Image (cartoon, rainbow, N blue to C red; front, top):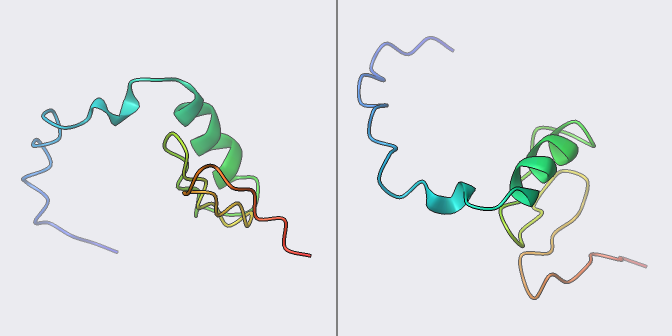
Length: 64
């Protein structure tokens, strides 16, 4: 809850190119509140709590 050892949070400007597109932003906000703060959408991985496990070939989790 309370961590005073995050003085190294200034090291996220090297491989943060994951935020290139925009769909990732519209999915991170449309997936977090959609079911829960478990949204993992980042291009083709909607590991959101909404049960959208499609991190592979964008396969929809249409569990019968």
